[PDB]
Image 1 (cartoon, one colour):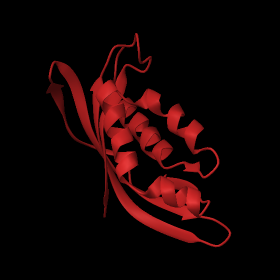
Image 2 (image 1 turned 135 degrees about the vertical axis):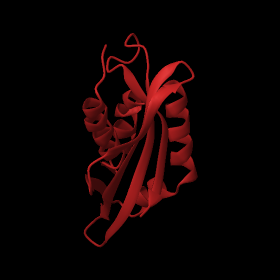
Image 3 (image 1 turned 30 degrees about the vertical axis):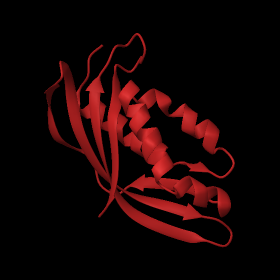
Image 4 (image 1 turned 90 degrees about the vertical axis):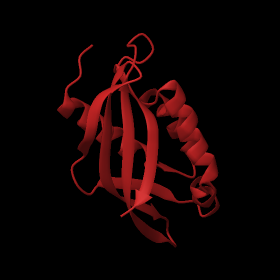
Length: 137
């Protein structure tokens, strides 16, 4: 297929938000529903990041609902060919909310994604996330 910068951005926006949209009940379904956003190596790294962080443990323990909204528009920091595949480094700030009847906590995070073109044979979108990095401010 074909990819536009603007299309890739809107897509990166969706993927970033989806990653922070789950709860103590549906986490497994939501987790798995997102695998399509990722490339082979991206899925491994994303899963690894999930295990290292304690987030899922607190969400379950405190039985929270996680949501997020884009704080500013996503931007392409850099684009070009990496290892034979056209790629985009996309960054977007977000406001994440962890809440329940008893708790309400918010975080300003910045998501940085490496997005690469892949075969539509395995990923109909034609692109996938190879690296998913979260940080503050």
